[PDB]
Amino acid sequence: LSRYEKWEKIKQHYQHWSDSLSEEGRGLLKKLQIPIEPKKDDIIHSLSQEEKELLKRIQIDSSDFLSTEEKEFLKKLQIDIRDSLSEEEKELLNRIQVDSSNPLSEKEKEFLKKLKLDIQPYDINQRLQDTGGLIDSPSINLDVRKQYKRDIQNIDALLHQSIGSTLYNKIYLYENMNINNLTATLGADLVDSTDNTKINRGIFNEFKKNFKYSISSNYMIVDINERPALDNERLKWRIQLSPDTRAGYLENGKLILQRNIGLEIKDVQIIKQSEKEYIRIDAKVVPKSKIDTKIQEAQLNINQEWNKALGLPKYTKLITFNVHNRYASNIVESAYLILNEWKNNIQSDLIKKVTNYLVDGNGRFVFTDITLPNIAEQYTHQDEIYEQVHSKGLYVPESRSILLHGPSKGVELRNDSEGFIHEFGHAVDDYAGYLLDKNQSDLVTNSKKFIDIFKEEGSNLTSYGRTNEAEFFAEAFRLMHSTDHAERLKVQKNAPKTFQFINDQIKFIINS
Ligand SMILES: CO[C@H](C[C@H](CCCCNCc1ccc(F)cc1)C(=O)NO)c1ccc(F)cc1
Ligand SMILES: [Zn+2]
């Protein structure tokens, strides 16, 4: 309508609802909009002096297991502990994170792994997104888990009034979004590197190609009137609700939408607003069940394809889509591309032999847009939260499963297929070790032979490869199967013993 007429009409529709909210209800909605942060002063006070000194000098961005949120908080914490010091110390501890980008020491690792338990904000919307609504996932303290459930049940009950049959087709709602919240990989290159006012057309095509549906597991907070973008908001969603979509009015002309929303992507276009290019995303709300049907149909389809390609029984459940968030369709469709690259770049007998071993152990290839600590193939086997990891990908020997987190980007990885191939490197290590001694099953990278190889060559490849024997093996494996011939040649030239060792293990596997 008129922008303000639309605002006043929606506010009127929800006025009784708004006036009727209890103090409890208003408090929940406030909490949801603005999460409570952990107390930095209290965290620091709880540390021993040695722990304080340890935290002062830790290279947080060298950790391999923290979420972005955990890292950013620890950085803010670190500023405070350092502030008693002085400028040289301050300036020094603070620019040999150049080539120094060393793996953390075991002492630094163990400290940070426990400390992360104490830095979680109480954030209902983040909890729903990280878990994809699987709020019983044992990735946070049980008592906090219970509070989240109570709050979420209560918010669900608050949001009982639908937008209705009168307004739904007379209004659009809006959401600005950082592309990095859907895909950090494409986000890195979305904007033209020489001219910030422009979108890279190739990356744009990649972004929209398989973007057909979207899920909100958390509560969307949408603008009644479109807000001009902040510098990092290059996505401008324009959303049409369904008559049955439940919502509540929020001050300053917003709506909070019910959680567990499905959205069909109707159109994706580059538009200009004030001499800058943005991506318009036109989306229509549909029942979430309609979207889940599409994901389940895709899961059946991709397994039917890959079971045949790999010579597995047709009914094998190998590939799983654990998909719950706003770039949903791309998580699904990109899995086909990732597996194609895997098959293209690795010998067929190797892929078949290793995958059969995984399947023999009820293993899965899990493609997901929820955080890895909330994937059962991890948490069923890492019962300590301090040992749970978020990362671009993981290999869990106990579940013989490869996990791949779609929305994030691995630092030294160009794409999702390189991450998957890295994890498959761990699977190779596992199966090769299993063959060595089927009775006491260990990784081949734990052999004295490879330990000696790592001690000699472990710094000769990637920075991340330095971490330990297993990561070195996986990194060497990935680089040996790169689409870039120069990278394959680098392993052969700079880590020749590792190159030989891996090829020898590949033969052992294929010949078993
Ligand atoms: C794809 O992601 C990796 C990093 C990622 C870091 C995870 C570290 C966890 N390792 C211990 C572990 C294992 C299984 C568990 F269940 C729990 C804990 C990884 O190495 N995956 O294999 C990556 C590799 C190369 C790169 F350049 C960037 C990231
Ligand atoms: Zn790894």
Image (spheres, rainbow, N blue to C red):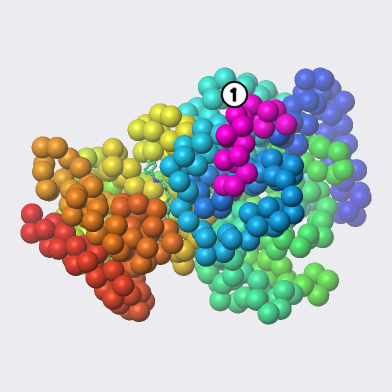
Q: Taking 149 as reference, is 249 above or below it? A: below
> Which residue is denoted by mark 1 in the rendering?
144
Query: At which x and y percent is residue 47?
Result: 61, 30
Q: Quadrant location of the C terminus?
A: bottom left
- Residue 237 lies, in percent from the top left, at 70, 57
Q: Is residue 344 visible?
A: no
- Residue 447 in sight here: yes
Seen from the viewer's position, the closer of residues 376 and 61 is 61
Residue type at the position of mark 1: Val
Give left or right: position of 99 versus 18. left
Sort mark 1 into few (<14), some (14-19) or many (20+) by Cα contacts within 10 Å: few
In the image, residue 59 lies at what x, y percent?
A: 56, 51
Q: Position of residue 293 (x, y in %)?
A: 45, 45
- Residue sitting at x 11%, y 41%: 438
Magenta stretch: includes residue 48: yes
Could you tell me what secondary structure mostly forms the magenta stretch? helix
| Residue span colored magenta | 41-58
What is the total number of numbered labels drawn onto the structure image?
A: 1
Q: Quadrant of residue 259?
A: top right
In the image, what residue occupies the spot 74% across and 27% down?
A: 28
Residue 91 falls within the magenta-colored stretch = no
Q: Is residue 332 left or right of residue 171?
A: left
